[PDB]
Amino acid sequence: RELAILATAENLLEDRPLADISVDDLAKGAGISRPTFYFYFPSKEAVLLTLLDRVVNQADMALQTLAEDRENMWRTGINVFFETFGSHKAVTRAGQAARATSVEVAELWSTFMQKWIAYTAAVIDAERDRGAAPRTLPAHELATALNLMNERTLFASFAGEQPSVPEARVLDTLVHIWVTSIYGE
Amino acid sequence: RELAILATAENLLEDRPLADISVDDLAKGAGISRPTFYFYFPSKEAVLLTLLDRVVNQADMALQTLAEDRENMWRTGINVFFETFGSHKAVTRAGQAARATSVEVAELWSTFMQKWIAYTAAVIDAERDRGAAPRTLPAHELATALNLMNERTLFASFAGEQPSVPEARVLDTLVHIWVTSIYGE
Ligand SMILES: Cc1nc(-c2ccc(C(=O)NCCC(F)(F)F)cc2)cs1
Ligand SMILES: Cc1nc(-c2ccc(C(=O)NCCC(F)(F)F)cc2)cs1
Image (cartoon, rainbow over all chains, first blue to last red; front, top):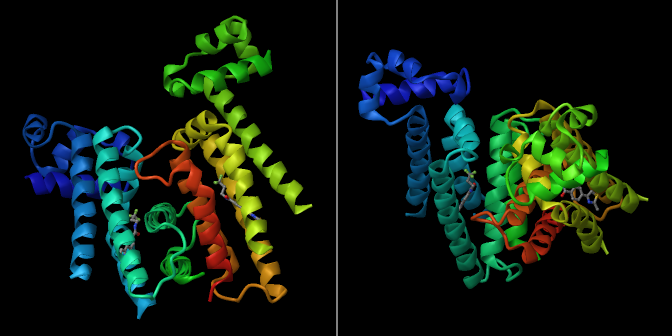
């Protein structure tokens, strides 16, 4: 029943914004009543938070799995986000828009971005320690800009935004900019 | 009176979101009544559109002025946006949030981003034609990712977002990533 509500909200988010979806909608698709819905979630907003929270953790776990040539290493890491978020475009789109109106969605996003940037910087620092990358910008600042570039450019591509890099070109585009800015210088 | 309404909306946007500002607020600060306000603008939303439209055109004109070493050339161009938007942070912040709710603000933003990306690509292409930059990524795709990185990273810095590059470091951060990704590979 919790799973059914989640699947239903993801299904419907493919067709319309969260605002055009009602508790009654989610309830119907899940095969339960409205008050029964309120036993699982306080609100439709809470349902989107849980969907985003699962997609973000799935990216984060895949990146932990990788952690356990240099161009390919970065490509494989960026690809976690391309495939994870790009396989859940409706949740990605609605979760990003909700950052504006939900402090819990904003804090969720912020917490994981900090984590991913800290880990990016730790890897740059290792590449510098081994003599493979030059000591140019402070690692954490470089990492932060690269992570934000990916956030905006991935998500603009997935949304078909104008402008955006075509989805079929965006992985290669981001990998080039990461490798050149990390190893260049 | 039109100028007074605009100055007043910019002043108040420094303190609170557009939603916490009423036509009555703008009218008061401008020294006119509410129906007199409606003679100048159809809505508070229209006032923000005009503010954004002036800041965007001021950046765009400064970039046209520049057009009339390689690291410094890119730095001087990125700086147009750092100084123009960074001198109008409240308008930047409210105008970006309005892209979600106003098609006219979305189309304005999109139109100028396309223009700035097209011009970035034309300069990369010239640098490649002269033998100074290598033919790596398609120029327009590289330009699009760099422009989106700047959009998100500048504006996160100006908003004091977590995460963000500190405002005092963001120009140097972006210049490094542009120069390395353009001349590297
Ligand atoms: C090989 C490695 N890759 C990373 C890595 C790769 C990509 C990202 C990344 O795209 N960050 C932005 C995520 C977001 F796009 F916002 F969803 C963050 C970290 C760390 S170590
Ligand atoms: C020397 C040159 N610089 C450019 C240039 C430099 C910077 C930008 C830029 O920051 N684009 C994003 C603007 C935005 F940040 F979104 F406001 C666009 C174009 C073109 S030719």
